[PDB]
Amino acid sequence: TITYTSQVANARLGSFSRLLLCWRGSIYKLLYGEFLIFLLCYYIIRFIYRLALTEEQQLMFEKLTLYCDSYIQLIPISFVLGFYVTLVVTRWWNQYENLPWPDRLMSLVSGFVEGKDEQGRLLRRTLIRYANLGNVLILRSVSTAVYKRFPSAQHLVQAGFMTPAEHKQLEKLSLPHNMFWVPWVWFANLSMKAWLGGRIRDPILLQSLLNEMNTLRTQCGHLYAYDWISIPLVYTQVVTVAVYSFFLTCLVGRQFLNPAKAYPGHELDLVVPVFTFLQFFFYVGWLKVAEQLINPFGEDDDDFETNWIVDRNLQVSLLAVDEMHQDLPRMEPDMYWNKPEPQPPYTAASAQFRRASFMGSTFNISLNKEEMEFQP
Amino acid sequence: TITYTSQVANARLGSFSRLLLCWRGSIYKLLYGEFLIFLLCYYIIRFIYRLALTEEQQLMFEKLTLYCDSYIQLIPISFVLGFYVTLVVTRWWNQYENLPWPDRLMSLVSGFVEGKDEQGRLLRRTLIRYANLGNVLILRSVSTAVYKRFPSAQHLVQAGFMTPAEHKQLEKLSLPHNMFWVPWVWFANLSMKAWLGGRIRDPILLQSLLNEMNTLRTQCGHLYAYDWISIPLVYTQVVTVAVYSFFLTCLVGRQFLNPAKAYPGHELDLVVPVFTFLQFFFYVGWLKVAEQLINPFGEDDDDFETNWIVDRNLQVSLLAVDEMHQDLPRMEPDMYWNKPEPQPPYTAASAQFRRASFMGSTFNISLNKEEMEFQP
Amino acid sequence: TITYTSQVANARLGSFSRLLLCWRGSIYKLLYGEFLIFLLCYYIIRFIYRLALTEEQQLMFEKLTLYCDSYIQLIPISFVLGFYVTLVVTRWWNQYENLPWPDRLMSLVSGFVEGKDEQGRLLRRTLIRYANLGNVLILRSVSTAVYKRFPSAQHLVQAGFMTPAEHKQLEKLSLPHNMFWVPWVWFANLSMKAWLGGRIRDPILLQSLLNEMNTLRTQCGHLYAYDWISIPLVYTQVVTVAVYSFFLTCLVGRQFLNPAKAYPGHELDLVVPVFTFLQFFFYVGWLKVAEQLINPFGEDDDDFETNWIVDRNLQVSLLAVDEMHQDLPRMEPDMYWNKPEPQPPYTAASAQFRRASFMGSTFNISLNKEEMEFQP
Amino acid sequence: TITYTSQVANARLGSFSRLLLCWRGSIYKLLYGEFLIFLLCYYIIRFIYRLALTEEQQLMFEKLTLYCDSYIQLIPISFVLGFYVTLVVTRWWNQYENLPWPDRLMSLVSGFVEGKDEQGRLLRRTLIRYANLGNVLILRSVSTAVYKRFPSAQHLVQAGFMTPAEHKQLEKLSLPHNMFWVPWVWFANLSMKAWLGGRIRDPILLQSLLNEMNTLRTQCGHLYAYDWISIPLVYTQVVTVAVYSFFLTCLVGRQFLNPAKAYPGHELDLVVPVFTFLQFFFYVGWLKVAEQLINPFGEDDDDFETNWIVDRNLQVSLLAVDEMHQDLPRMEPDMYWNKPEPQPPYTAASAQFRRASFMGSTFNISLNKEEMEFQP
Amino acid sequence: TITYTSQVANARLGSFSRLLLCWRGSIYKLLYGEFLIFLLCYYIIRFIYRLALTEEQQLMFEKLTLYCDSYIQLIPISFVLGFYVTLVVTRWWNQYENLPWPDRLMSLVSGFVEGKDEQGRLLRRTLIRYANLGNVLILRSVSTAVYKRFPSAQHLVQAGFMTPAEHKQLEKLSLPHNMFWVPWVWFANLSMKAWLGGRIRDPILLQSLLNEMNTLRTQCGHLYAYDWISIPLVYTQVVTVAVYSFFLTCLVGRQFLNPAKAYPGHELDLVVPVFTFLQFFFYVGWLKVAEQLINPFGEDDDDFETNWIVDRNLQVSLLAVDEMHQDLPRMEPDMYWNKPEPQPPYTAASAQFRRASFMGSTFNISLNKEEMEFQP
Ligand SMILES: [Ca+2]
Ligand SMILES: [Ca+2]
Ligand SMILES: [Ca+2]
Ligand SMILES: [Ca+2]
Ligand SMILES: [Ca+2]
């Protein structure tokens, strides 16, 4: 993830222009290789046409160049890129939305599972650990970074996500499919035992806990679905053919023909097809948007920071259910205890953001005494 | 936020034309700087071409101008702007939808947490204060205006959003990540204590309270997500390249060539490229839509009024849970107590809006006696 | 609202052609003023060019006309209109979806709040009245028609939406923001008192009531949001500039030049630029779609019938919770009491709509005896 | 509804080509009338131009034809059709999604409402009958086919959807608005009586029943909304003007001019403007998509089969709550009772669909011994 | 399903270029037949024009070719394909989202339905078997692969999805509609009996079980809806006409005319219309996206693996509710038991993915001492 939110807070003079000076996650970094190949092919064709070809061969090449330049179209490529890239971007955001966060669940485990004794601590930590374990099992299935960190279940044991007993239980349960679903079943059974054992005081609280846990299960299922059900290969191939064909055609149609022939549109021979290069940056960059986002769990600069998410989730969840269980700041009368209309102050830097309330769009409508009179 | 809802209530003669006379949040305010730079560059090129260049240099420049004007295309730029700006606008509205409002929660805290004594008052105020504190922690993380108002946690203490005890508790819990999640865990634990202490009469009410609070947590998580996971930089760079390249090409391709040469389309030499300037306003304004909305928590005219939202939420939430707790208007027979079909009157100004009921699209279908007879 | 659903039930010969004979909510009614202005400007330019201008001035004007006609483009305008109008239409439907209906809530108030005595009647009527009052407070904030009907809270008292005691309570609670949220807090507190007083038999029923009421609160909050957070002014100005600039350019570029000059495309001098007028109807009508829908709570023909909704909601809600409370039709064996497979008859007019069940797309697949045999 | 799902299961050679041989719900059936009118007008213009017009009149007509053919544009029409038709298709699917199915509710009524005696049977049947009655009241309000089947409430009585007592109760409750909402209030009151009478054992079950019933109410409200709030007439008129104007222009611009004049593009005089006819099929068919779908409750081939849905819902709901109440198949050990990893067999025809599990996209990543070592 | 997620994890040099070397689910496999037919027709026309036609016939053909090449347009086809294919892709993903997974339900059945005795085992297995049976009944109705595996209910009995007693019960209940809904009613009745029999301890747990089961019912209803309510045939025919007409026109308009005539754009006679073939691959591949996805339950390479889903669901669900019922790994202090801030290690391969926390976009804003001072 490359965050530039702070740089685009305001629509300042050349706000997006300044973003062209970025390297990480940039268009430049994504297509410089393809652009260099295109550059080399274009100038190989230029040298061949200018030097190797005979006069008749040069005339045939100049006819082919006019034909190819005539057969370059930007509407179909722009359209298919628009729709395809929009699909990729939509799926990208949906995949972020299906990253499981334990925060809702950990609030409920901290609140509902009772006991400051070692047994209550162990129960709360085990429940939230099952949640984190389910999350990491799916993430190591879909994220290259997470997999490289946990290339085997034994790595999960060494890293403390899974106990040796949990590892042994998983091996006993082995089916020939991804076992990421197991910790949810464990969570449901352990929550039930907690309720039957009196650690959860009422089955409505158990219902809430299982509802939050199942929300996480649905998110994990969606991550599995996106990882398994790729955008149909035929669609990806169609967009790829459109782009690569446009520029293969440009390799001949955008050659600078010999000025001596004075062909329409070839009066001057600049060596650099600057406009063609700008079209390359635009169209191939547009395609690189999809190439980066199609699998957002890879190692691209703008792929999701899955390892950070795993670490943060573990730290926060264990703190929430263990140290923060019935550990509250003292409850005392607040600063506005007997102030009907509290008005927190503004800083010198923030004074300009104090606003009057918007009362509704009708607030300023003017009506005469007669207009406002009720009729029988 | 620039509200013009009242000005566009009706589709009146030149309804949108009148909006062109607005300055705050206007296209003019957003691109006048870029337009002045473009204006200066265009006329520098004009003066250089007209005065400095020799006859041969002028002919070469006139060839380059014809080439550049030939290589100006509006379909790719319009397409990429359409899709990109639509993405930005969608994310903009989603970010508004993830601004947390305490209204649902405060109704439940006012209703369910019992006691007119000082302890009940303190409990209700503390719960709703935890909600407001969570909200402000995330908002100061994502909103420049809120941050400038609360540039440190100590500012939150001075402003009355957090007690000194709450501040000390937060410092004790410090992890190397944003601690905006803490007040939710506090809320869950305090609600649990209220239930165990008899201030909440039934665990179903506790379940409802925690459900509303967790809804707010999800909204805050979404604000964090949008602040962290920018639109991929490559996409922003692609759109920026498209626009800036179009107009860099225009800087040469839209020059008024010497009329004496009588080039096709250069018969008359107007000094102002009015059409090019209109295209600038259109395309760069379209891009400025995204530039303003990409981070709606900045200080642009049309960015969200986060400080007002924080102040209003605090005032309303404290009033709802403290002064309005079991404080109801007298319950008395309404004006339509024994009126089967109440017909509230209309004013002279509103009489034209009295309507007959729409009974359904089938209501006026005509059928003969034979057509309506049931068959065996 | 102009309903034409019945007229377009079937795809009949010239189904949409017949809709061009409509006046109310029509394109004609929305742009005739702008079209007349455009008509007058076009013919003023025609008369000036034909009569006032000298021969040299006429030649300069004919050059400018060719230039302007060359610089007319329909792709950018069509694109920006497509995206902008789609945004407006989406927001329009979302605003309809956020109009609160009390039907779900009134079913629960009728069912759950017990007692045929005067106290039960008063309690049910007061609860549903709080719902209707919240609805009308927001609607009078966002709807010009509702505001003109209720230009002050005292009008709400005279119309029977609010009691004098409720009015006094509201004035006591006054904060410098829209108080539309107050009746929800009152509802929560009154429902709690009903439960504690035994009128609501179980807290799960209280939970359901408050859930439905909070759904209405969220809808009202969305109405407030749409009324406050306009589509960014810059976007509206961009689309407006695109359209108005297209047609300002047409005012010169679409002039009929003197036939004697035999300019390419000006061989014949028709006086009416019929195609330009059709383009005006199309593009300015497309923009008028947005101009009407951008604020659907105004007084346009196709704005929502908010006053009718308020009246109907009041009548239905009071009937549902008061007259229909435990007032059921006699429960008796239905016509199909001992008929395993009930087959309600068809009329002569409806006989053609009797269908066989669709059993699924696989139902007709043919397989040989060998194909259907299970393998080991 | 024309179902062709089975015909397009696979992407076979000319899969969509074979669909052009369909008549019911076809493009041919929808526009043959308009196409015949267009055909007649085109050839009337041809005959007039070829025979009636004088030489000078023919030259004027040939100039007008060149002008009109120059002023034919396909981008605006394609754009506006794309956006408008997409809106219609979206609303079409949303309307299908708002067709109420009693299946969830009928499972809960079958399970929760106890008693195999006549009273329990009557209670279950009455509750599910109220659901079906609400559904049919709205459907007869919005569906021409349903209305023609039930053109009066008395028809609902004769068809067995409503008892005479229910009819009398409805007439007593009459307000000047659609009464489709009444059966929900009856359902809520009858469910409450069932709970108070001990037929529903616990208020949580009552809560579930009312939640499912209210889901159906929301769906019915959406059907009402779509029936009432048409797509704004101005938008429909805009698209209609675009299409009809394109083809009115084609009526002159696509005439075959006299070959003797050798106009550019009129060298050969084919009598049939085949390309213009293909454009007619395309554009007018695209518009006919909207014309059919704009009201999907009419009698078009591809309108919804509302009568079938009503009949099926009645049959299934009554069977589910009456015959299937506590009528279960014997519970016995399944075929895989002591089989840890059940492997149901495949047929000869299905053997090729047996697959290995997809274990996740990371499953095949290769790492060296050093790469997989944890670091301190 | 063709999964290529692992191949597109990163935006590597020619990432999408490498996907053009795929056969299964490829563009090549989907249109080679149509392309061969197009190839044969094009060269038959070439041979006829070059050999059979006389000089006058050749001149007429050359005029028709110029006319046809003039009448080839790519904007309407690209537009209609964009919108239509987007609709198909949206419906495709929605259909995947409506594939029922028993995981949420099986967690609740494993947790809530008590007893390690044979009766508890039978009850849990029967409940989850009803869920799987409902799923398979709908899937065999909509999926050709599933149907070919289970071409009759007796096949479901032989495969162990349904007992002989369940089969007999289904035959007794037979109505003239798809009976896929029956197992939900059985589930509701059996869950109710379990609660009344004490196997489910509290009606809130029963409520949760039925809520999850009804979610599955809604998904199955959606699968039925998509299978029944095809995309309107007229829309499919419109897109098909656009594509097939474009290429039928190309069959004449893209012929290589005799070079001796030196027609504009026919200077050189290449035999292969390479650009036309690329346009074929692009446009017909784009259409093949829809042709494959329109029914994603067929046997295409990229259709869903329904049989695998059925097998996996059965195996996992039975394991979860039977072997894993109250079978938990030992609960023991985790590796971070007394570690406030757990820091799981990284591998050598994963060290580069360790990140600092993103604290929010405001974290780096700089303010002076005066700017941060609160004002009165
Ligand atoms: Ca990636
Ligand atoms: Ca901003
Ligand atoms: Ca309006
Ligand atoms: Ca229809
Ligand atoms: Ca398929």
Image (spheres, coloured by chain):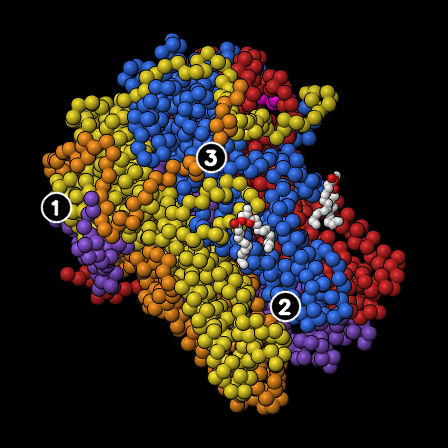
Chain colours: A red, B purple, C orange, D yellow, E blue
Same-subunit check for callouts 3 and 2 = no
In the foreground, E80 or C103: E80
Distance between the alpha carbons at the discs numbered 3 and 2: 47 Å
Q: Percent position (x, y) of residue A165? A: 55, 11
Residue type indicated by callout 1: Lys
Residue at image position (67%, 45%) is A26
Residue E362 left/right relative to C313: right
Helix, strand or loop at label 2? It is helix
- The residue labelled by disc 2 is E64
- Residue D196, picture quadrant: top left
Q: Is residue B275 above or below residue D156?
A: below
Q: Percent position (x, y) of residue A255? A: 78, 60
- The residue labelled by disc 3 is C366
Q: What stretch is highlighted in magenta?
A: E339-345
Q: Percent position (x, y) of residue E83? A: 51, 52
Marks 1 and 3: CB-CB under 8 Å?
A: no
Residue D164 left/right relative to D366: left
The chain carrying label 3 is C
Q: Percent position (x, y) of residue A355? A: 43, 51
Crowd tier of the residue under label 2, counting other residues whose Cα lies within 10 Å: few below 14, some 14–19, many 20 or above: some
Helix, strand or loop at label 3? It is loop
Residue at image position (23%, 36%) is C342
Residue type indicated by callout 2: Leu
- The residue labelled by disc 1 is D172
Residue at image position (51%, 24%) is D346
